[PDB]
Every structure is written in C-alpha cells, then in structure tokens.
Amino acid sequence: YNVGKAEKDGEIRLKNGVAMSKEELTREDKNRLRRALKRKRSKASTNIKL
Amino acid sequence: YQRFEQAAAFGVIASNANCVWIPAPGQLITSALEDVNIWDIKTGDLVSKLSDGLPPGASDARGAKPAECTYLEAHKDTDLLAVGYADGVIKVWDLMSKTVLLNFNGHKAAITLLQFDGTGTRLISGSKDSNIIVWDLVGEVGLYKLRSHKDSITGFWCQGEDWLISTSKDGMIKLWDLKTHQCIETHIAHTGECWGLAVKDDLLITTGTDSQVKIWKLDIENDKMGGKLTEMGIFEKQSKQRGLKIEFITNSSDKTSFFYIQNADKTIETFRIRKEEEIARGLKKREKRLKEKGLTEEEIAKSIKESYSSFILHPFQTIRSLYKIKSASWTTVSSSKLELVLTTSSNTIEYYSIPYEKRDPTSPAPLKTHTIELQGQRTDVRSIDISDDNKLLATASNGSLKIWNIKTHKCIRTFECGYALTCKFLPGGLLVILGTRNGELQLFDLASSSLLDTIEDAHDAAIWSLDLTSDGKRLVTGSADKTVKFWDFKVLKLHHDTTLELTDDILCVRVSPDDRYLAISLLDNTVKVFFLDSMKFYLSLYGHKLPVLSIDISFDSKMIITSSADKNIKIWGLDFGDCHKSLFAHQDSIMNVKFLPQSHNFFSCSKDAVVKYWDGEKFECIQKLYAHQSEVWALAVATDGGFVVSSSHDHSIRIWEETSLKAGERLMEALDLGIAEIEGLEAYNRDMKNAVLIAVNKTPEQYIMDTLLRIRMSQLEDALMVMPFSYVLKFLKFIDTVMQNKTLLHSHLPLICKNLFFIIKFNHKELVSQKNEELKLQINRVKTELRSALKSTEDDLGFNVQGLKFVKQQWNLRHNYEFVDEYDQQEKESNSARKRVFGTV
Amino acid sequence: GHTNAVQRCSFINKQKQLISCGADGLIKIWDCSSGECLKTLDGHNNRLWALSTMNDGDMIVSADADGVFQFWKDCTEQEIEEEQEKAKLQVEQEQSLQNYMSKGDWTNAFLLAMTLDHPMRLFNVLKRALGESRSVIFNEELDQAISILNDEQLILLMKRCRDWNTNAKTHTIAQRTIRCILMHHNIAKLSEIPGMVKIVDAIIPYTQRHFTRVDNLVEQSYILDYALVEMDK
C-alpha cells in the first residue's frame, strides 16, 4: 500500500500521509498547494463613435 | 519641449462614492473623482475642494491614473474626514486645515466602508479584498486583521469595543470577537449576495439581491455557543432590485425610529418602527379579526409568527427620483417633518423633505427642497469647443448644452437641446451651432440666451460631424445619411447650398485651415480628400483597418492625421497622400486628435482615459497625461495653443495649461539561554523553600527543542560533535527537564533518543571519568523514563499487530475457500496474492 | 446535437428554453438564447412521436413507440432548496467545529470532524487530545465517542489510521486510535464490515516496521546502563 491521490475530488492527499479537505484549507494554503502542484508537474457607426 | 499640467478640473458634483452630511440644511461632502467637494446645500455653490496635491502631468507625478475616492466618513465631534480610495488607501483629512494627516495602506482593493468608533480614536475599514482592518489613529498603525469573509465587505456594525458584526458579498453574516480576533458565529443571511446591514438595539435588518428582507434579534450576551443571531421574520419591499444601504434614525422627543432601504433603482423606500404598545394593540386586533374568521388558536399563533414582520414595520413612504440613486443619508429628524439627502449617478444632489403627522405622512409625495445641478452636466459630454477669445468653453451633452468661463470655471448659460453630437463656435464667440442625432441643426445665441433657429430636416440621420471654413461664412456637415451638405450664413439664418452624396456613412469632416482641402472619413475605412473650391476629388487615403474617427490638418496644410478605432494614428503627406508613419498610440479606440496651433505637435485622446502629447516631426510621445478615470470623448485646443481642454465619461472637464550562525553554534546559544533560566528558577525555588523567551512566548524546554527540530538531520550529527563537553552536561540537564513534561517527551521521543545516544557515544570516555554524584542521578532518571516512554510506544504497537492479525484470521475462516487437495490450494493462493511489476535489466 | 430525426419541439420556460424529442429516444433541453443543450433526459429506448407540456413545461409527458410514458416534473427549485438547507447546516457545523477546537472540547470536535470529513482537523483533535492524555486510551468522554461509531464512520476512521501509519512521524496517533477501536468494539463485528480487512491488511506490515524500530531504540538505550556501571567503578 502506497498513499496516493485522494479518492474524493475535494480531498487532497500527499505522500507523507497528510490529507486535507479543500473546505477546511484557508485561501492562502489553497494557492500555496496549487503552486506546489505546478512545480511537481513541471519537473515531470453609433456603436463605434459613441 | 514644454510640459502640460492640469490647471483645473470641474464639472463633477458627486462621483461614485457615498455622501456625508454635516450640520451647520447644512453642508454636504461628496466625492469628485480623486478629490472631495464640500457643497453648501442652500446656496448650491462649492465651499471648498480637497486635493492631496501632485497635479497630473508633473515630472514628480505618477505614471498611472489617480485612484478615485470610494467611501467618505467623517467624525463630527473631532472634525476629521477619512477618505478611502479605489487602490485601498485610507487618508485622514483635517476639515479645518484642509490637509492630509494620516495615510494607511493595508488593503489590496477598493475600500467599501469606513466607520469611526464612538470616541473617534479607532477606525474600522472594509475593502473589496474581503478584509476588515482596525486602525489606531493615535498610534498610526493597524491593530489587527479580520480574514474570514470570502468576498467584498458590503456592511459591518460595531458600536461596542467587544463585538462586531460583518456582512459580505458571499452571503454570510459573521459575528466577531474583537478581544480574540476570531469569528464566533456564521449564518447564511441570503441565498446570494448580502448587501445591506443595519442594527438598532436587538433589531437587525439585512437586504439580499431579491426583494426579501430579513429580521434578526441580536442577543449579544446569549453565550449559548449559538443564537446570538436568530432569524425573526421576512418582509418584502416593493422594489425588486437589491438593497444597497440601510440606516436608522431616532426622534429624540418621540423616541420613534425610521430607516430606509436604498435600492439599485430610482427608489428609496422608508419604513417606520412601530412602538411596543402599538405592536401589542395591533396583535390583539388581528387576533380578534382572525378569531372572527374562525381560525383555530394554533393556526392563529402560527399566522402571527408568519405575519411577525408586519407588526414591527410600517411602510412609510417611497421617494421616486428621475435619475438612479447612488447614495443616501438622513439629515434631520423631527416631529414636524423628516429630511433625506441623496446623490444620483447622473452627477446631481437632491434634498428631500417629508412632512408627516403620527403614523402616516401628510403629502402623497416627498417635497424636493434643494438641488445642486448647475455646475455639472447630467450626461457625458460628446463634443466641446473653445471660443476664439479663449474665454468661453462650449460643452454639448445629451439633453443640454452648457457654456463655461475658463477663468472662473462657472457655468454661465445652459441650453436645452437634442442628443448633441458635435458643437462649434461661430467667429466672434457669440453664437454656437449643434449637430444633434435626430438630424437637426440648432443655433443658439449666447447674448439672447435662447435658440434662434432649428433646421429639423437638415439630415435624415445623425449628424456625426460639423466644421466651419476659416472665413466662417460656410458650414459643412457630415451625417450618417451618406451626404455632405454645404450651408451659408445670411442675415441670421441658414440656407442649404449643395449636397455631396457619398457611398457610405460619414464619421468625420475636416476643412483645412486655408479652406483648400476637405477631408471626409467614411465607414468603409477610407478618408477622402476634396478640393473645397471646386469639389474635385483629390486623394483616397487607405490602410486603416477600423473606421477613422477623427481627422485633423496641419496649420500649413501639409500634414493630415487620421486616428481610427484600430488604435493607430497615421500621419500622411497631403502633397501626394503618402503615409509618413503609423503610430500604435493607445490601448483602445482613439476618439479625437488635434494639432497644436502654429506647430506640428498634436494631442490624442482615447477610450483608455489617457491623453498623449506627440511630436509632429520626430513622431515620439512627448508626455503621457493620466488624469481621467474613464473614456475621453472629446478634446479641444486653444487658438493660441496655451492650453488643452479634455472632457471624459466621468463628467469631468480638465484644462491642461502649458508651463550567520551554523547548526551546533545555534544549539549552543539555545542551551545557554534555556538552561540559564532553568537553573535560575531551580535556584530561586531552592532558596524560597528572559526577554527572548517572553517575546517568542515559549518555555525554556520548548525553545531548545524547537532549535533542535530546525537543525537539518544531515547537519545534526556534525552539529553535536562541535559541542564542547561543558555543553554536553547542559544538554543532559535539558533532557532531564524534558522528562517531567510527558507531553513534550512523547511528541519528540525519537528525536530525543537519536541526539541523546549520539552524545553519549561520542564522548563516553569523558562522561564516565566524571565523579559528579549529581550527574549519576540524572542519568538514572533519564534512563528509567526513556525506557518507560519507549516501552509504552512499544507495547501499543505489539498489541495492535497481534490484534489485527486475529481479525484477519477470523475473516479467513468465515469467508475464504479451503481446498483439501494441497496442490489446488497453491494455484488459488497464487492468483489471489498481490502482484507488482518491476523493471528488470 | 441530435443523433437522429427530431420529431417534436415545444417551448418551455416562456422564451428561455426549448425541448425536443428525437427518434434516438433522447429528450434534450436547449437554451433558445444561446442555442446550447442544458440537459439531456434519457428514459426511452425507442422513437418518440408525442410530447406534451403544461404550466410552461413544469410537467412534461413523453410516450415511447413501445408504449412507455415518462412523466417528468421540474425540480430545479426543489433541488436548489435542498442545497441551500444543506449549505446552511454545513456552515453551522464548520463554525461549531472551530469553536470547539479553540475551546479544546475534543470529545465534541471529534464528532464534528468525523461528520464533516476534515482529515486535518481530525488529526489535530486526536493529536492534542492524546497530548493531554500523557499528562483509558485518550480519555473517558472521547473513548466513549469512538465506541458509538457506526460501520461507515469506522471505515472512514480506519482509512485515516492506515494513511497516518505509513508515516513514522505520525504513527503514534494511529496506533492509539486503532487500539481504542479494538478495546471498545466487538471484534467479531469489525471483521464482517466490508473492506475492513483490506484496510487491516495494509496496517500490519507498517505496524511491524514500527515494531522493529523503537525496539532497537530500547536496545540502544542500554548505553546509559553501560555508562552508569562505568561511573560506579
């Protein structure tokens, strides 16, 4: 068993085992996680006149 | 080159902001884009104008459009005015000194609401960025931020230092605890956006997008973990549009309360709060009516709850205005009458007086007592002009024509006209001619202050452009009817001379200064030049992708400029019609271009709210003028070239006049600080029988532990080797003190073990040599507790592995197939067993 | 957008929308203003010849060639009301959860986290409730709460325990919760819960690794004993 992607769409699950529901995450965290996702994928006449 | 700076700005009475009424009908404070105006209601004249400074066009001036005022709040007792700007900047203004006192920058978007506390020492600001920040005026700092809301703050209520209620565009009403900086309660006020919030005692009212209006009782001291906000009832206002603002006012003599619901339409609906006895009296009467109707007692009580709102609220009166309303505020409350002041979106101020007696008002409609309308134009100015004397500026707008004195900036005369599109002075500065959208030509006389003549059938369609010859005896008008018509001035009346039929709609017509060329722009993207005297075709300029909107010809009749909706300015040679250069000038359509007199330099204005000064020979942008907030529709250049006048969609007319430690080393420092405190307290306690730690708010054990965590493991072993033995005894004392705290020990048990065992192993020889009896006892205490903590984690693991194995085994007996033949079981287990694929070389 | 011939068409919701039936048997609701398919209703396996509407299409009747009638009723307002009520309850639960965690009412915060499915808050509730326990498994109230958990909640909790167990920095919270489940639940019932054994299968191999570690830490700890005997000499 390897902890992988969350089965629920709303949930976010990381390889370390930390799971976060998107509802609870604060907006700054949501952006931070979104940016972290980017890095990992990258490594792998009338109308006119008036 | 010389620099152009904003000499003056006028024509704006009330911009996109709220209005503040101050007692002396009293004065009114309203926003004028980047500046704030103080008006006198009775006289209708501007008392003063607040400008921070740094006029547009200066070298020190910024390269972006000014941030307009968005919300105004004044504290009456202290004569302080707080002005919020669309960039999230709060400026505190001194009304007496008319100067800026404080400048707060904490918001990332437009400020939606400001509010002084009762004592006037703290300012709460809400912004479109969904944050509420409390500012300390005396400290000139931000105390704390409130960051629960997920959309723009529409309204909030805080009359006490202890509690605050906020409303936001996400549909939530949130109760805040100012001493804890946390949100305590959250309710969905409305299905969509929640816009209005007004609180009077326990009574609370909020407005959503629809006509539904909710009532809430505010039992602040409920302290049940819930119910500080509970829904009372729903009452429907007549206006189906959203409610923007709600405000209470109380009559001191009669303790009666009134409030309004400013709608997005042209309606303000006022309401009266029924007194408690009247609620009781009404309740009995309705119960008798319902009882007479034969309804059961249970049904009556439920209906009374359904009709709860009607008992408290009485629709008082509805104020109807010709123009959409932008903001409103109570002015005075009295038994005789009730007065309101509002600002419309069409740049005017209206004062309403409501005389009333007892329940209902005396008049069917409110009385409009005062209006401030002379110094502005209701609709946007489509065309402007400057007289030859450079003293009178004619501004033509939909429904009205106004003339201004450039020196006093005050409107002299106002004329009622059609949807004016083009306006120009006749020679002498005593007459004006308009080209209306209905195809009419209107001639006004300034001295007579009346319209002399109208030519109803001048054109079949809109008259887009209108120009005069240098002599001023001939008139040229270009219209959407696909014709150009020549007119003569004969004593004064206009006579049609000739008609030139073209193939497509005409957008602009220009006559060269010397009266030789006539340039006409067509909707098929082409500019046609004709010889004025003979009307013989001369050239057909081509290459513009979108229709040409303005044309202008140099004073020497050598160059012709064409600015089109394709964002390009093209400069041509009239001798051969060759294009000298195409400039990608603006970020949107360019509406007007004008040559400076006696020079080839020209100005350009576009929908991007930027006026640009160009050089005619070098074809570079000399200066960028950022002062307008919206589209610039028209432009005009003085005959002498001393100043340029621009009129924009924001109802503003602007005149431009020509002028370190490493790991281990950090750990040793941490040990010194923590163990200095631990040893100090231990000595103090024995006898009885620092700044850094206080700042971080951590115990000595936690402070050292955190330093250990921060050290990267790849550096930890080398960090501990650098430590002297004297610090190792300090480290051992730290581990001893951690042992008493069982919470910390089990939080970081593996880390403690790795560092402790490494320390002992590295310098075991020196540790054993020491004959300190105290040290022997520490290692005994450290040893026993480390085992028990490790054993406790050890026993829990062993219990679970054996228990979970039992659970697996029981399921196998009940729900696993067994094959008596051993060979048949082998293949079954192989198939059921998990399979993983590995790459092999 | 129709695969086959369209045999009926009628306007619904005044000018806003149109409904069409095709020989493919698919009823498609389009938007007149944008000309786009908002919804597709599929209750037939043959051609549709007839389509009746009433109250601007609040109820729609379509008959198959086989003889099957589908009586459709509008439920947009019914659906949105439920979502509003669900959202209103969720907003209450979220706020109540934040209050309990700030107050430290873990026995209540645990229940809310379980219903709301907030794995992070659930971990913090158990983590700092365990920390207080250091100073039967968690405490009397919270141990009772775990015992009451039904089959659905137990499966959800054991899934979190599995994931926490994989990490050596967080396994301690997983073991005590698993122990709490074993000590306060009928072991027979846990086996029959579908999918529990597959969850249990992943837990044991990691539990054994954590067992091998810690046991080594105990072995290493006897350097203190060898230190003490040396100092005694």
Image (cartoon, coloured by chain):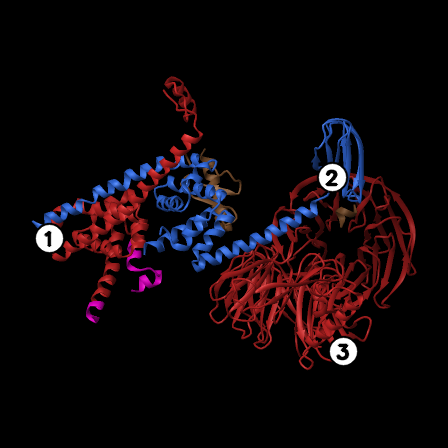
Chain colours: A brown, B red, C blue
Taking B490 as reference, is B163 left or right?
left
Viewer-side label of 2, 1: 2
Three-letter amino acid code at the position of disc 1? Gln
The residue that mark 2 highlights is: C72
Three-letter amino acid code at the position of disc 2? Trp
Three-letter amino acid code at the position of disc 3? Lys
Q: Are marks 3 and 2 on the same chain?
A: no
The percent position of residue B672, horizontal first and vertical second, equals 23, 58
User: Residue C212 is drawn in which quadrant?
Assistant: top left
| Residue C35 shows in the view | no
Rendered-image quadrant of the N terminus of chain B: bottom right
The foreground one among B9 and B289 is B289
The percent position of residue B380, horizontal first and vertical second, equals 74, 58
The foreground one among C69 and B771 is C69
The boundaries of the magenta stretch are: B684-704
Q: Regarding mark 2 in the picture, which secondary structure is present there?
A: strand
The residue that mark 3 highlights is: B358
| Residue B404 shows in the view | yes
Chain on which label 3 sits: B
The residue that mark 1 highlights is: B770
Viewer-side label of 3, 2: 2
In the rendered view, would you say B761 is above or below B118?
above
The percent position of residue C128, horizontal first and vertical second, equals 38, 53
The residues bearing labels 3 and 1 have C-alpha atoms spaced at a distance of 98 Å
The percent position of residue C50, horizontal first and vertical second, equals 81, 32
Q: Regarding mark 1 in the picture, which secondary structure is present there?
A: loop
**Crowd tier of the residue under label 3, counting other residues whose Cα lies within 10 Å: few below 14, some 14–19, many 20 or above:** few
The residue shown at (41%, 34%) is A2
